[PDB]
Image (tube, rainbow, N blue to C red):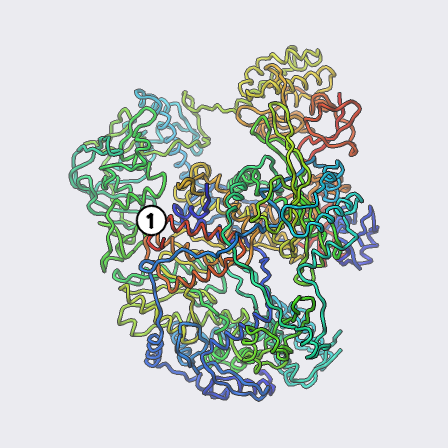
Amino acid sequence: MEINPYLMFLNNDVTSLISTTYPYTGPPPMSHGSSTKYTLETIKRTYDYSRTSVEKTSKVFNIPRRKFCNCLEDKDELVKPTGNVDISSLLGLAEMMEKRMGEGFFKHCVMEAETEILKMHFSRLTEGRQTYDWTSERNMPAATALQLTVDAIKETEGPFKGTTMLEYCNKMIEMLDWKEIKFKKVIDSIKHDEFLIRALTINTMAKDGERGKLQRRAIATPGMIVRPFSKIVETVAQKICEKLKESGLPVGGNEKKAKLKTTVTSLNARMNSDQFAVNITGDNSKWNECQQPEAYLALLAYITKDSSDLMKDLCSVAPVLFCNKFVKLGQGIRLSNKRKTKEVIIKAEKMGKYKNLMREEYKNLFEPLEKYIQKDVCFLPGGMLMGMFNMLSTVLGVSTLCYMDEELKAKGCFWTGLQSSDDFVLFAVASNWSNIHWTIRRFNAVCKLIGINMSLEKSYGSLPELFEFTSMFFDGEFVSNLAMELPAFTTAGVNEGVDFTAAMSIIKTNMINNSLSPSTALMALRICLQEFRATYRVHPWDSRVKGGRMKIINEFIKTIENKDGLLIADGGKLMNNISTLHIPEEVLKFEKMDEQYRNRVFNPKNPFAVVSTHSFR
Amino acid sequence: KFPIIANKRMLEEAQIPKEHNNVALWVLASASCINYWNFCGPCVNNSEVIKEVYKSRFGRLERRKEIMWKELRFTLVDPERMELIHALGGETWIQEANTAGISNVDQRKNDIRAVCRKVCLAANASIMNAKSKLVEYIKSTSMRIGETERKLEELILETDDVSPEVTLCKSALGGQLGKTLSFGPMLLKKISGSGVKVKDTVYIQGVRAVQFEYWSEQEEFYGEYKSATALFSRKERSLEWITIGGGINEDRKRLLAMCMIFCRDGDYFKDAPATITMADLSTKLGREIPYQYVMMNWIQKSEDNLEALLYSRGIVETNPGKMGSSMGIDGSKRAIKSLRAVTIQSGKIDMPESKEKIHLELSDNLEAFDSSGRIVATILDLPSDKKVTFQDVSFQHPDLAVLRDEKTAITKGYEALIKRLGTGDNDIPSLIAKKDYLSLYNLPEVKLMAPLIRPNRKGVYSRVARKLVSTQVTTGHYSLHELIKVLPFTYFAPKQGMFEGRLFFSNDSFVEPGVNNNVFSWSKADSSKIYCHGIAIRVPLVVGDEHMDTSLALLEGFSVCENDPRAPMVTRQDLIDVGFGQKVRLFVGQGSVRTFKRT
Amino acid sequence: IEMKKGKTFLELRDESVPLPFQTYEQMKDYCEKFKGNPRELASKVSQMQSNIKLPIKHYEQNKFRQIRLPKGPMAPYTHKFLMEEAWMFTKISDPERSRAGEILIDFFKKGNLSAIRPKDKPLQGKYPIHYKNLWNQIKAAIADRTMVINENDHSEFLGGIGRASKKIPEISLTQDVITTEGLKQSENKLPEPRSFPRWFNAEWMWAIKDSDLTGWVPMAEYPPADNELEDYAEHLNKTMEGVLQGTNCAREMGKCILTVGALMTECRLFPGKIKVVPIYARSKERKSMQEGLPVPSEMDCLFGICVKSKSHLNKDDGMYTIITFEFSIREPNLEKHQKYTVFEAGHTTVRMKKGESVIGREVPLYLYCRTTALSKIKNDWLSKARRCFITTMDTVETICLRESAKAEENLVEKTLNEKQMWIGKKNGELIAQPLREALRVQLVQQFYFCIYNDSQLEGFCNEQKKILMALEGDKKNKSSFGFNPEGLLEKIEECLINNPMCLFMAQRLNELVIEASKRGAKFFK
């Protein structure tokens, strides 16, 4: 006998079994690292996708500046990625989109973003995945580096009493011109150029956690200076993407399916009996190595052209900050003797000192870039490595999709679709099995004009019924999702009265998005409960455990009868179910907990979501 | 060790000693300190404040508690609820939970149609008394329909809801019809034309032959399936043209296949698939079946059969200007290739109405005939028998319901064992006080329950049960619960063998002493009750100590004793090689360990 | 009010600009006044479309091809523990001694381990003497009631075999020193390619079987119910659990869980120390020898032992090392067992029914020695093995609702007991089983995914999806079209090395396309 766990795909669909193809969600044990090898290949492919050779030495660093925008050359083999952007076509597409949506559209959106920012407190910057400290030269949460920056400002030139985003930004600006800056270390100070560099430094993070593909080997990790301007630009781009029908970035699921079906139905009701449509599942390649902040700057200028000069100048900050971005090279190379009994370790700044020892592969990837190196970093003048400006990239993609001219109209063909950050789905329309090819080629050309490329080994197409988008494998029916998320206690331990409620809410959400079903949700619940217990080293009372926390619980338990009312953290049992997720177990056991136990737990006169006497400050 | 921070005065004011029982608890502190604080600490009364502050959450809980849960149903798409929409309705399923509104009519329709299906099926057990047994079932079936205790002899008529079962049961009542038809689950209707019956043959395996019938003239109809309309014309055993206005893939596919069978178009009416030859059984247990219903059943088995049937229908390449009204193999609204003589469109085809009532004539197989044949309904167009709990119903005539299962058999056996007690002589307590257990091994009720016992290894079960019975009687220490539990096994003769710890019936269920189970459970503080699948039963007597002595109801030749961890854990097998004065621990259930000593 | 400007910022802004513009003001004026000239834009896009040659294939005139696998020796066993060739001693479970340190000592008391005395000469191995002396030291430590090992000679070696050397500061470096030592850049090694494994099917089949014992995996309780939905969910979960617990895959899952639960604590409380840890599991019920029905039997089982090296889990991405001493009663094969050093440790006993009694038949005994490393992330990934079920539960439920929705009624039991699913081919003919029996295959697939998880597997799973969608489109007569299939074939062939799971899946996928060619027109032979 033999086995083949794919024969079930013959007499069945794929929307029902595709889940079996990918492992279960969780932290990737691959340990995708960010090494000097990886940092250098990326930079090379970046400079190469720029099909030009022009440069211009600066005046703030005495360094060349590869200006890869509006200077396209090397037309040969243009099916491969490109990064040289054309401003004329960009502004033309922006104008088309404006005309479609309306005239005072960009103005209204920028006004909303402004007013939202005004009442904003700089403290918001503490809400971020991670950043890069410019003093310790490391990566940390936002709050830590923020405290470092504010206390350094205090130590050097007095405190920052703004308590607002705008004063913070202006303080950063002023600091750009300070000659000497101080900070507590292991105390030390620095000069103007070094502080500038540090502020324009970036570090490659190894973390890449998500479903689909973990292509984020070297996800960026900027500092704190540019953070608020990036937040502002993202707020504006978000306010814009909301009004756009073909923008699935800000949210997903129910709304996403609504957008899908609206699009499909409008299409079906649009064309005629002679036309026949088609779909394409596209996947933009190198969406980070072909997005240039210069085009973003010109676009923001064209946007704010008619608005308060305040926003005109503000939106023009993060772009220039990305036009000049020093990239921190990872850990340096290491030497070794033949038998490997000895091994030197060297940093990146000195690899230019032993370039003779290194093997030819590393040697042909290091010399052409030595020009752009200063001490240990690389002056990257463009590209976009961070997972930032995703909203803005999506806006540019939608601009690409809202194109239409008379050359197409004459042939009776057109297109439309939807675009995520770097993944999209196209729907072409025509009346011949050949004009479809012409339309596809036209679309690819207009996309390549502005660096937006497409893959050939990962982008396919077929008739309209079948496609895929953001793991939501759409079909004639039976829309199947695969974005099943889950919590993680060991990595994020907060309290024994919040994690469980948060997990219940998460499961509820996943059910809403149809990524989970009743039985699946119940199994996940009974699994997360055990994970929680094992995390905090707690068990029920029926169990014959001998752990520390159980000892006392093994003696002060007979003093109660409302075992049902007991808390999970205290030898309790579950009572919540599908229809009782939004309801925390506490609210569900209040009237049931013994008066003595309820009161012992609810005592604000204690040494320390329903605020329990279960917190771990 | 002490990562968790705390306050200092808050600690001393509560008098929290460190290392209470070798647990430090601690400025810093451990986590166990919280348990010590919530188990032995200060007492407040802040319930009202907490509730007021968390009013929104507790109002959500209240609302939740203010629900009347209803049934659920699997189906598709043709604020206070947003808090629960996640648990209210998905996409394949939905729950009809309501809040304040009540109207019991459509549920009543489902009930009446279900029971009509049931009864009409029940009448399909003979060959001659069909109509008679049917009508007598009807006359013996009353219901608390809605709120009124009505009978099922007027509802079938007073109601106006077309269905195969309603019609099949009302024709026998000489009731009015509406000219509607039912070919399987599909609903049909005539529009124009007419014809006469004609016979033809069809092969099976390429050698045999079977006769079917059809019509030779032209005639147009109005098909209709779940969320799918249609119109079509049949001519000479073949489908000429057809159109559809309800856009769904599966619905359209199945409706088209059913209309094709209704038109008998296709080559599988000349020969048959190689799957049918596997059976060639166009027959029931003792009845005959046409070819159409056999083909249909063959479709219901798998959609591959549907695809094969549709391929039998010619497939061609669509021409320009027709994509908008073309079709695909999978119901695709438009395609570069479609099927012959098809037309897709949007908007459901408005169905006509016939205001002419008639009466039909039932046959041996209950098939009704209005005129010129033209069968309107039958049992063949029904689903298989589906057991469903019926309430608000009374069904008196035999064949009403088997009402006989191993579970119910055991329940009744135990009820009889309990009643036999009867607080009198020649009953359980008298024989106990008399110490005459042998008679217990000869009662009638145990003899009635014996057939429910696993036969292969009943001797050992009887041996063990008699052991327990005698050991609890002679000494006078016993427990009526475990006794009654094991009694049904003390009928056959004892034999040697290997026992495991469970007594298995014939239905693969089991029972175990010293523990509780769904089939049989009980507990102290309610000893006057005995649960059987949750059904609480009463004891004709009262006891406060007759049950408290279970030291001999766990094992056969042993007795419980004081707990002792030093004693080694053992199994049920090595017990034979133990001695006296030798304590031993052993599991008595799930994570339940107890110590035992011989005798 | 306004954003008070500095100087350096303005200089940069005036510097970093497009080519024809050298000041923010010129670019700004050009932008604020940009007008639309769709004609030049159309000409430009047409010129770009002309100087581009975008191919568009339809998968029909230019079909796919079978994949070219690597060539060389067979891929060996990779998982840490043993699944099919394993063996375990048993004993009764005491809730007062439900810990590794106690279970191991108890197992050792009866002296069945002390009888394990491997001879000097092995069958196939590399460093037998180290393993043997280490086993003796392990027994000595257990005798001392402390799992610790004081002497560090063998563990040190076997932990340093990977990498250990001196380090010279860069400042103490010159040119003559270099020329003397011949220093160079550390060449980086690549994984060697391997062939198709010819033992995966056997392990899969064995896993699909039903284990004599049951209850390997522990689970939580079931909360109350308040409506039909929760009742249905609970019923389905109970059914699936009762079906799965009786398998052997569950045994391995519980073993991994309980062993990682101890290793994650030893790497936390005794870092930088050498400890001893058992490889054990816990059961709760068996099947009668006289009846095929379940019976309560709480019990503990010991498959082997695992030693731990110094583990701090804060440096070198938290890499640490372990050493495995597993028991087996099945002699090895040279190919599958390459990383394993094997011995022969006396004999043992097997117990089987004989009428109404139990008997014992003595057999030989083998000892499988192997070294391997781990990390904190791998621990967090293995501990969460139960999640596999969730995915198996979702595969069961999508199917049990779709149908239930087409007919608008509960068809759960009907589909579970009737719906046939292809599982494999026997004697050149397909094999089908009910869903209730294919749950096992689904779960084993998810488990193997959880074990051999790696970048290669990520790429394989991310790429096969396109082939699956193309095939589905083929089934339903849709002119699937692409741009460069051969490039995808290469993308998939480049990620096939030293990972038997990916190779097995690739082979089965080729077989699938072959079998479907009988009904599809997009694949070569």
* Front in this rendered view, residue B54 or B41: B41
Q: Residue shown at 38%/50% (left/top)?
A: C514
Q: Residue shown at 67%/21% (left/top)?
A: B480
* Front in this rendered view, residue C501 or A398: C501
* Front in this rendered view, residue B557 or C223: B557
Q: Is residue A553 left or right of residue B419?
A: right
- What is the three-letter code of the residue carrying label 1? Arg
Q: Residue C49, percent across and down?
A: 34, 74
Name the quadrant of the N terminus of chain B: bottom right
Residue C428 in view, yes or no: yes
Seen in the picture, residue A282 relative to C382 is either above or below; the reply is: below
Residue A553 in view, yes or no: no
Q: Which residue is mark 1?
A: C519
Seen in the picture, residue A77 relative to C385 is either above or below; the reply is: below
Q: Residue C131, percent across and down?
A: 70, 49
Q: How many marks?
A: 1
The residue marked by circle 1 belongs to what chain? C
